Amino acid sequence: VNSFSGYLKLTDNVYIKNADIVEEAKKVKPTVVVNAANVYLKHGGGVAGALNKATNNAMQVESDDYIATNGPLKVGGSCVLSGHNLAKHCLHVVGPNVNKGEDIQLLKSAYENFNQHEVLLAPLLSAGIFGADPIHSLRVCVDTVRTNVYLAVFDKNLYDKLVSSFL
Ligand SMILES: OC[C@H](CC1CC1)Nc1ncnc2[nH]ccc12
Ligand SMILES: [Cl-]
View 1 (cartoon, protein in one colour):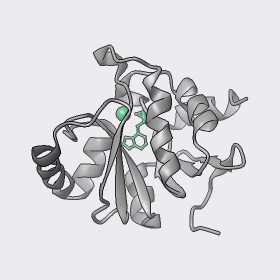
View 2 (cartoon, protein in one colour; view 1 turned 90 degrees about the horizontal axis):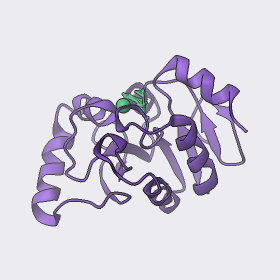
View 3 (tube, protein in one colour; view 1 turned 30 degrees about the vertical axis):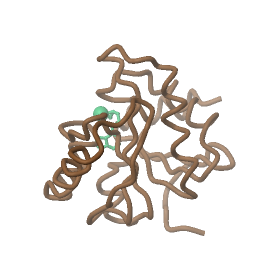
């Protein structure tokens, strides 16, 4: 039993809700919140900009030190950093950005990072400003993630389409 509330159950392990991931994280304080990161951990917009803003830029400060030490992530890769005031940990995961021409096949590799964590609050990877089809992202999530994932989402209209079209 966990403290996630109001989610629709899609499969044994995947749950979904129309919600603002910032507000969800602040309420639940999950062990792991997933950020929709880029390889430079530059948290400008979308989920990343919103999460970073909620940390008063502490996420960006920590991220800049991470990059200075380790260099950029790989598309499809991830790193674990602090969750600041939002969660114990933040798993920064880089899905392919279609608006940069990146290979959508890398979306499965991106979701594989979730399997290293028993429970996660997460957005749909590569959706929103990353330019992928969210119906596809949800399908890849369900077919790749085996741990317990709580998908937040932001767009109410999009949520209804994802539910009604789910196979
Ligand atoms: O595919 C991720 C999704 C995509 C379209 C809704 C823009 N973005 C978000 N999902 C959940 N919470 C969020 N908070 C801020 C942004 C955000
Ligand atoms: Cl977005």
